[PDB]
Image 1: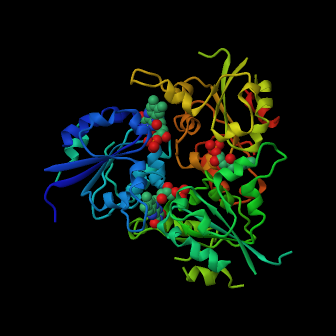
Image 2: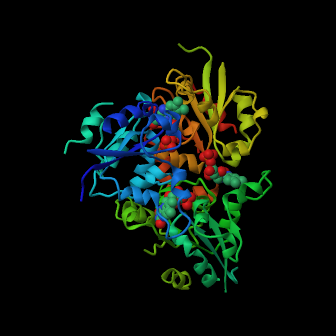
Amino acid sequence: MERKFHVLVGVTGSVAALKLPLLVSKLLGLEVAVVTTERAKHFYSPQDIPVTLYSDADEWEMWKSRSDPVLHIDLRRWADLLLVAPLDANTLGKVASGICDNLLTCVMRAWDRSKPLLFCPAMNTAMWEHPITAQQVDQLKAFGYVEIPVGTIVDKVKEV
Amino acid sequence: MERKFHVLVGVTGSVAALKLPLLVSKLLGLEVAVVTTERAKHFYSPQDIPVTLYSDADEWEMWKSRSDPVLHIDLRRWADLLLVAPLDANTLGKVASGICDNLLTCVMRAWDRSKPLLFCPAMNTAMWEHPITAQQVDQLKAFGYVEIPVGTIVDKVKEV
Amino acid sequence: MERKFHVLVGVTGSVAALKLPLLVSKLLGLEVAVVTTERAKHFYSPQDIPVTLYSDADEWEMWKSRSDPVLHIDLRRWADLLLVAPLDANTLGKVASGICDNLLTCVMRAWDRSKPLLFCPAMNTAMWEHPITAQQVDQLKAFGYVEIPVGTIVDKVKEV
Ligand SMILES: Cc1cc2nc3c(=O)[nH]c(=O)nc-3n(C[C@H](O)[C@H](O)[C@H](O)COP(=O)(O)O)c2cc1C
Ligand SMILES: Cc1cc2nc3c(=O)[nH]c(=O)nc-3n(C[C@H](O)[C@H](O)[C@H](O)COP(=O)(O)O)c2cc1C
Ligand SMILES: Cc1cc2nc3c(=O)[nH]c(=O)nc-3n(C[C@H](O)[C@H](O)[C@H](O)COP(=O)(O)O)c2cc1C
């Protein structure tokens, strides 16, 4: 039951999000939406992204009863593909450790295996030139989230 | 030196806490107290729980000098049994990784082996139908915290 | 290119920071600076430390453009030695899991192998008398951060 593809772009606190607009305008048969972390918003302005932006607070403001919706859940059953550009050293360790403390990491931890989750770490030489990152990126591969160590990402989205 | 049993119920951010009142009114020779996470309080109202509710802020407001008490510590030497109903996918990963960033997870990480800590994960099909949860729940078993994958829990509390 | 040694003292939320001033006044050819966590500041007052104190907020207030500086980065290229006295059970698990959610843990996760990072866990009998702490302290040794399970620390700083 798929027509226009539903892609969900997750954004974290890396200077890379500075470029996030580019990704959106490009990536936009696709049909997108971005979900951010708070710090990520430190690299771009909402207006510079012509799409629906879901944030932590967004989830809780719409829930007041068991009848009410569960944004992170609602978003997980809506995306056909979940791209996370960029994935910071922090969220990597959160995901690596099944830590859902924000709307993003929760969408991920509730993800659908059946659907694809391509990510692309984007830290700094230092943070990257450290161990864990490896023991974690592949530890993350254990769930096969298609790494990507703009452009490259863009094309890679499709690849039907 | 035990008369009336001291049970400590921990509550996290799962819709399950919606039921938390039930547990309390039932579980209440037992003598209880609940310790929550902030988000958990998103599923119940304090008044609907006829017991002392300890929260993060509670710890710090009472400490101003080395002489002063350490709530999370004080609570760890007071409970005979520590039930955590529900344990969310998030706190599981916190506990799994020895992460004490809130009054709950700290009480746990300072726990007494000598005393029992029965817990019961309570996420959603998705979040649960994911890996880590397993590599973690049993990773958590390594410390033997008696899983429980209301009712069932209730009875299980006792079982002298 | 080293003259006066640059030591960076990290402080976390353990009652031990109560003593932090001592360390500073002593440790001060050395030339120091302290980087704290928020909770840590619950055990000492800034004024009681005659040095530049870097805090989370400090990083973000100085960054508004890609041209702008990256405190946690700037601090990582400036320290010759990074001592973390005390390292709480919490930050241990953060570091263990490559979790940079605050200025401290970020400086660490971006650390320079080439430079030394001596730390000294400082929790409580309980929190310490637990497993993970071990599977973690040595898991932390994997990156060789020179444990130290005031005084002892002080001398140990030097040891040219
Ligand atoms: C100016 C600046 C640039 C940063 N750049 C990066 C980066 O490129 N990659 C990374 O992993 N972390 C970077 N960080 C650290 C993260 O912002 C910090 O880990 C944050 O907690 C991540 O939060 P999040 O996971 O909610 O987005 C940077 C911090 C600052 C102040
Ligand atoms: C309406 C709603 C329902 C949620 N239900 C669950 C759940 O049933 N299980 C779970 O692990 N997380 C659930 N979450 C996500 C947690 O609330 C989020 O992980 C939170 O950070 C946990 O915080 P805590 O550990 O401080 O309680 C839900 C979020 C929302 C908004
Ligand atoms: C009075 C008091 C004393 C505490 N002492 C310690 C301690 O000695 N060691 C430890 O690991 N945690 C201790 N904690 C718990 C930490 O403060 C809590 O884990 C905190 O989140 C650590 O935050 P940080 O990593 O940002 O500093 C204490 C808490 C309180 C209220």
